[PDB]
Amino acid sequence: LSRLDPPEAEVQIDRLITGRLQSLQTYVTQQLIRAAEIRASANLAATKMSECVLGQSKRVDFCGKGYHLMSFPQSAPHGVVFLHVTYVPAQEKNFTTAPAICHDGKAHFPREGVFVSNGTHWFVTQRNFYEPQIITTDNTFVSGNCD
Amino acid sequence: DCTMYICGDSTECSNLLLQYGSFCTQLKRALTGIAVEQDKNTQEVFAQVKQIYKTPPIKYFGGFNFSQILPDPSKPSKRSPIEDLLFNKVTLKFNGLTVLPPLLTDEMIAQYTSALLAGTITSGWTFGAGPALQIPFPMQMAYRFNGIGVTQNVLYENQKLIANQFNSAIGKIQDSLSSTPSALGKLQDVVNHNAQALNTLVKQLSSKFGAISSVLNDILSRLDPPEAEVQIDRLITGRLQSLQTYVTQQLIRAAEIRASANLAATKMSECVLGQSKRVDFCGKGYHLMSFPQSAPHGVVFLHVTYVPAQEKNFTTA
Amino acid sequence: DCTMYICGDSTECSNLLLQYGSFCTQLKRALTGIAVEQDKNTQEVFAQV
Amino acid sequence: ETKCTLKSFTVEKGIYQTSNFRVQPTESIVRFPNITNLCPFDEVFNATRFASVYAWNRKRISNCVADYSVLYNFAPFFAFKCYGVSPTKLNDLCFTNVYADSFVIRGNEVSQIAPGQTGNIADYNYKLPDDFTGCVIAWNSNKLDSKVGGNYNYLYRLFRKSNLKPFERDISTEIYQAGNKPCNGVAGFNCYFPLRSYGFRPTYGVGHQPYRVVVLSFELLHAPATVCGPKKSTNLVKNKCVNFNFNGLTGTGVLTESNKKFLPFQQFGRDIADTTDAVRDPQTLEILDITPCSFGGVSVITPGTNTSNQVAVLYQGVNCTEVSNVFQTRAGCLIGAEYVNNSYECDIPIGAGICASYQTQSIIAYTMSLGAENSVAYSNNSIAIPTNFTISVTTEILPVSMTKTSV
Amino acid sequence: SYTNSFTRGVYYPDKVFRSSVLHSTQDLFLPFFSNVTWFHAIHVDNPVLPFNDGVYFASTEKSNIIRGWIFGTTLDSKTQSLLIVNNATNVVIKVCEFQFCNDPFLDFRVYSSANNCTFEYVSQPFLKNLREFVFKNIDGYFKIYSKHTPIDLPQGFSALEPLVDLPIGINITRFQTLLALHRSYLTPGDSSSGWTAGAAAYYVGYLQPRTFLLKYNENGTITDAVDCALDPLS
Ligand SMILES: *[C@@H]1O[C@H](CO)[C@@H](O)[C@H](O)[C@H]1NC(C)=O
Ligand SMILES: *[C@@H]1O[C@H](CO)[C@@H](O)[C@H](O)[C@H]1NC(C)=O
Ligand SMILES: *[C@@H]1O[C@H](CO)[C@@H](O)[C@H](O)[C@H]1NC(C)=O
Ligand SMILES: *[C@@H]1O[C@H](CO)[C@@H](O)[C@H](O)[C@H]1NC(C)=O
Ligand SMILES: *[C@@H]1O[C@H](CO)[C@@H](O)[C@H](O)[C@H]1NC(C)=O
Ligand SMILES: *[C@@H]1O[C@H](CO)[C@@H](O)[C@H](O)[C@H]1NC(C)=O
Ligand SMILES: *[C@@H]1O[C@H](CO)[C@@H](O)[C@H](O)[C@H]1NC(C)=O
Ligand SMILES: *[C@@H]1O[C@H](CO)[C@@H](O)[C@H](O)[C@H]1NC(C)=O
Ligand SMILES: *[C@@H]1O[C@H](CO)[C@@H](O)[C@H](O)[C@H]1NC(C)=O
């Protein structure tokens, strides 16, 4: 506006405006795409907050890798960190397993857990912790014969 | 590469394109970000297991038959007949447009799929929540039936019928997938869209963009430098816009593929690595187990569903 | 419609737009894809039964 | 180069793309069709008998390649004067028509054949236009057009009512009515014959001997040009990307033999992407396919200046047979690293299942390991029951909001 | 008369090779299934036909019935007109500004009284004996497409090859066909002729600017062609 005359600088100003508008439309598009990405991430984070912190979920790896127990949130200038408490089994041992037990001509199945055997012995245990208990009628039910 | 896409073998064209700014500096950066994101999406669904598991040599799990999902030692490529059928059905040098192959090839994804299959068949769900625990397959089926409310007696008694039904379903699913040619549509549409976008971006070089000709040499060998610097600018702006819109389409499709891959990884973790109580998240009906299968650009989940039938009327109180 | 939105009732304008390449083709293809997607999204929630 | 691309001084560990590798062509070839239709310049300059000055012999030249060099096969001519054009660059242009006007004149009248000049020849016999863009050649012909007795066959007009127009011919033999006396076809007082004869004899000096003058005038009307200069030619190149200029089709690439049988009316072929893929040779009937030579992208796999400075180069999507341990992969070809046979944990991704790292020494390259190996014994009468528990903590970081900005 | 041209009137739009691909181009073609004029009963009452956008000359002549062609603007004095005369083993193509009579004829080359020549383009001669020609003039280049195929227009497909192209541009608005007879009728300005000979029929069809989709096979020849304002499927 100080070197060239008005009627010949109008085209230059128009080209500059076109360039600066084309460089800004792309920025707005990138901002929209990143805003949609952040919206999806925030929806996922809110879902995890509701299903992990405000209660216990039965999902596998939605509230941590393993068996989820609880979750603690922590803030961050642009996000949230979830600390998931996971119960992991360890120190497993080999045992003999059987579907049912046939006694008195009737095939009895365990209510909760399975029958474990360590050699000429049979007990009932759960599926997450080894607790040998005698095979009684409380933890077993008859459902026919072993035919 | 904007130095070659917009300017075909010209130094003054590159000098004028460098004057436009750093459009290429962010375009090639967004493209590399898309590439890294696509290479990472292949590790959140197939690379969930830490240790590779193998199948026992004795192929007798209790009455079931998994010959169609386990890798076949006859074929050199370690894949299953279902993976071979899915691989033989997905139909797959320029002016600066290159294609980079993915990190995980079709063999490593196959090994991850085989490891996940071994973990979900031999160990059940303990391979995805800690140390692997050995357990017979019929007892795993009894666990999965008791998890939804059905007693274990119907499985321990009618085991042969369930095994025969599972074998019939595994044998019929191949014919069902081979009957409809549009079964592998979600994996072919993305490849078709990518091919069409690439072909269009290459073909749009022949467009005049308002100039006399599309090739810079013809412009610069038929006019004068002061009269052949605005005709080159038209082509430069046209190709820059055609590349910017292409980068925008690639970003949108990459976001869509990222969402799809996140959903697929969630389904892999909640259906293959354990049993879920969701209604139609691991198949339509009562979910029991899920088997993954690789594909050059995706994953196919085979969900085993137990459905009641032959109901009868009774009085309730 | 590219022919009417940009080149309304002008044959010369349509001939000038024709040399711009397949921008209009890809635009209408994306619009048809959006339409098909919007018509399909109404069948994954209400047409489950 | 990586520091210049990233605009920093302490680069991190990873692979970074900086520039692209391009093979520059060594030579440049240009092949145009044969030169067949040589315009009849020999029959104009080396004719058997030239015409008079007033009846200057005019010949039209069109639809033929004009070789402006055959004009200098003999060379004593003193007047090779070109007006409006340069005698050297005559082969760098094309015109629609070439008019050749030949005539014999005296030696002192050679300078009169020029735009603007006047006299006794270029006033009533053969006048040149003012804006004449052409070439006037003139050479002595004493040995051919001089008789001892006298060569009185060449005539010239001396008297006329008014001057002529540019490129005008007058062949009238009417008596010049000089005075008011009406001439009755007889010669005498105030009634002179306009056409006189030349007394060409070998005994003349250097100013009155017969001189043959040809005038080549170029016409460049809006009609398409059919008279172009002689096109040059070169040799062919094999297994090397050079610059080809086949009959207007210009490009850069390797011209390799193939079996793409073309049709007799077509010269080149375009692929599905409208890119030129094959082109005929303008000299021999043989199809040549155009192929891009070594082209791709260079990437520096640097472990970061924090550890060391030894970097490795990677050419992506291009074989490294043409233009530090060279190793060919499925995702490209890397130099500066040695291919290790033991699979470790992937650190720097490369592609196709190959990753680089620092062994500690030099950059390595190994097939990435998918994990450990553990095969449990599957038995229908054995189970693994846990005994102990472990309470672990897992971190999961997720962004929520963004930076609110406005322009 | 008036007949229909089902699937004929196609040619190569440009001198480029293509292999097993589809190419859509907006060129000047003859619309498929159109109303073309079949003048079989006009044995030289033969007015000259216009030359707006080119002509499609189809000939099923027995043997050497067509002797040449004339393409003028007004066929008057000082009017550039391109004449082509096909002899036994040579062809003569010239552009003459001379006036022509109503029906020029060859009997041995007396067509008209006036004579004035500007350019000449002699070359190789052009001519179950179907002979198709497509004559057009764009960008000052008079192009001809020739094809000689065995067999009325059948339901087959045959492309036209750009044999000859002349760098000359005239406002061609006339069209004259040249027959042959043995009655020995001299033409010092004659306006009528006629002789019992074989079947003589010259098809005339005007071209139109349309978009055509051509399929090129592995050999690079046109086998399938689709118009774009004929049927909804097209
Ligand atoms: C169970 O026995 C197998 C085979 O001997 C062995 O590999 C495995 O480690 C054993 N499990 C435990 C928990 O010791
Ligand atoms: C198996 O475990 C029970 C539980 O303590 C024990 O009483 C029994 O002796 C064990 N069996 C053998 C063979 O040691
Ligand atoms: C599984 O099925 C395949 C093909 O039907 C058969 O070849 C194989 O023997 C079967 N395996 C078992 C254990 O039944
Ligand atoms: C139960 O009774 C209703 C009413 O008659 C009938 O429609 C229905 O089919 C019956 N259910 C079965 C399983 O037969
Ligand atoms: C050009 O001339 C050379 C040498 O006479 C010959 O080998 C070649 O075939 C000619 N080219 C054509 C197209 O006739
Ligand atoms: C460099 O290494 C030191 C030592 O481990 C570390 O403290 C520092 O954060 C590293 N810096 C970068 C940029 O990696
Ligand atoms: C590179 O060239 C070598 C030598 O011919 C060949 O063995 C190898 O397969 C080539 N690699 C690629 C990716 O083309
Ligand atoms: C062609 O035109 C003539 C005269 O205009 C008419 O009689 C004839 O029906 C037309 N044929 C077709 C197929 O339109
Ligand atoms: C007439 O035909 C003869 C026979 O080939 C040929 O030699 C001659 O050049 C032709 N003349 C004209 C004027 O076409």
Image (cartoon, rainbow, N blue to C red):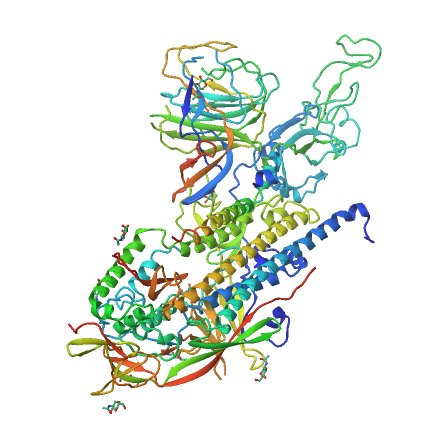
Q: Residue at image x 82%, y 15%?
A: D178
Examine the image and state in which quarter residue B292 appears: bottom left
Would you place residue B253 above or below residue D374 in this image?
A: above
Is residue D63 toward the left or the right of residue A67 in the image?
Answer: right
State the quadrant of the N terminus of chain B.
bottom right
Residue drawn at 81 percent across, 52 percent down: A1
- Tally of numbered tags: 0
Q: Is residue D49 left or right of residue B303?
A: right
- Residue E55 percent coordinates (x, y): 49, 25
Name which quarter of the figure residue C2 lies in. Answer: top right
| Front-lying residue, A79 or B182 | A79
Nearer-the-camera pick, B237 or E156: B237
Q: Position of residue E76 (x, y in %)?
A: 59, 16
Q: Please, which residue is most extreme toward the front here?
A: B317
The answer, for residue D346, to whether it is visible in the render is yes
Q: Is residue A84 left or right of residue B161?
A: right
Quarter of the figure that contains the C terminus of chain B: bottom left
Q: Is residue B5 above or below residue D5?
A: above
Q: Is residue A102 above or below residue E70?
A: below
Where does the image place residue D171, in percent across and percent down from the top left? 69, 19
Residue nearer the viewer, E103 or B162? B162
Instruction: Say which residue appears at 54% left-offset and 29% top-offset.
Output: E137
Q: Is residue B96 visible?
A: no
Q: Position of residue D1 (x, y in %)?
A: 60, 71
The residue lying toward the viewer, choosing from D404 and D59, is D404
